[PDB]
Amino acid sequence: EILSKKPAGKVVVEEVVNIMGKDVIIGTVESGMIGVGFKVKGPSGIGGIVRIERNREKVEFAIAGDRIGISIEGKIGKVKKGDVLEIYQT
Ligand SMILES: [Cl-]
Ligand SMILES: [Cl-]
Image 1 (cartoon, helix red, strand yellow):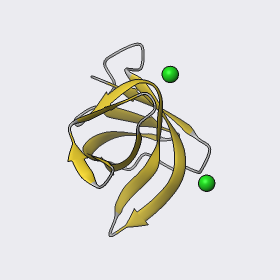
Image 2 (image 1 turned 180 degrees about the vertical axis):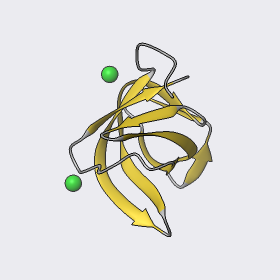
Image 3 (image 1 turned 60 degrees about the vertical axis):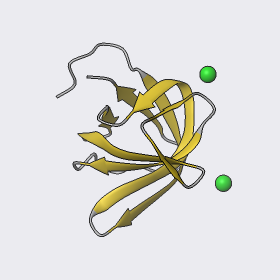
Image 4 (image 1 turned 120 degrees about the vertical axis):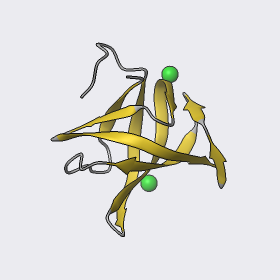
């Protein structure tokens, strides 16, 4: 469940791949910011950010303009290239 009203950040999806059951999203933070543990509001589900990578490095958070890879726990539904995902700190 998402307990906040406004997103901490938004991510535009560049590529989506499913690998051994987990959704990995490649994309760029469009605004605000995201951190490990934040929640992803998808089309039909809410996911948790479990890991973020930027330039092949593990990072705890990312901000607008960062291009990143994201691992999500939870089934969030069908995400496609071009989707903009809302990310909530709680
Ligand atoms: Cl592209
Ligand atoms: Cl921005």
